[PDB]
Length: 19
Length: 355
Length: 6
Ligand SMILES: Nc1ncnc2c1ncn2[C@@H]1O[C@H](COP(=O)(O)OP(=O)(O)O)[C@@H](O)[C@H]1O
Ligand SMILES: [Cl-]
Ligand SMILES: [Mg+2]
Ligand SMILES: [Mg+2]
Image 1: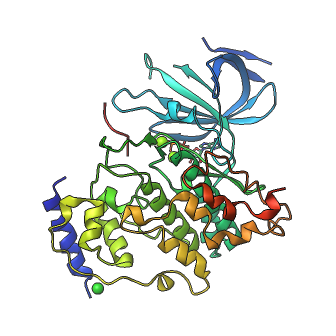
Image 2: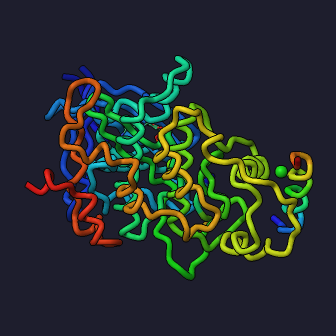
Image 3: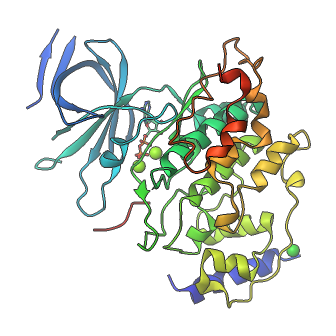
């Protein structure tokens, strides 16, 4: 599990729920 | 050589007691029935021929591909909030060996009890929340004093005798003695209860992951459902972030240094008093916020949690169960249980419990 | 989620 790939997914998801 | 004869069908094995030096003795039991089954093995209920007492027999396959520490860990445990290992024995997947664990039988779990209230649309009364959480923290304080981390704390692993309201921690198939300096597997703990450092893939975590899991149990009991659901790690971390807000760089560093340089979107925290129902007791909210912390070293220790103001009602001499009976034994702390912080005895043992 | 490998 690469940090880069994980953070990439997390960043994408957080942008979506971001007010 | 398991001799199975008839009295009612009786099974005889030579089994080794859980405590002391290995001195195996003949054990006879009857009335066997499955009370649980999985890909790990089988779990049976049975009746000891001699005493008539009920026991559970957890049958687990000897998987040589993974570390099997469950037996060795249970054998050194002896506490009122941890399920007792009476005996163990081996038996026959043909041409393969199974480990049989004979435990005290406990009829319910925290999960099953909580599920009753959920489908009834009622909240678990605070008194039971206090009692169950307190006993959980006691068992954690105990196993942590040996350096043992459970690594699978969740409602399904918390056995209940609802008549006496006694909670017993079970399932040590994931448990391990953590050694500072030796890496551990990060993909551990069950979904919904995995600490953030585990989701971030930390291999150097400590026993404080058990405290996070406990914080999730507490929150679940107050809420009526899991607080951080989600199928994957990202799904769960999002739910966590939606409550705690985006972790700071220092917090990310405390969890896993390899993530310190990513620019995560900055999501604001949802205030705890807005997370739970408006009827929720303030001290439960306070306790929960001190368990569900990003920084593992900022979380309360189990012994400190026991001393928290939320459990003050349990230290009242006049306190009693809703059914009429007295509360279980809550104050019989040993020097070992208190080894992490001996001065906490002043709070943990009320004056009326000194006599 | 199993424990560590051997
Ligand atoms: N000592 C016991 N007495 C009664 N039921 C038990 C006992 N131990 C476990 N169980 C039940 O069987 C289930 C599985 O036990 P567990 O040790 O957690 O197995 P697993 O490691 O496969 O999850 C538990 O959720 C619990 O409901
Ligand atoms: Cl936001
Ligand atoms: Mg289990
Ligand atoms: Mg297990």
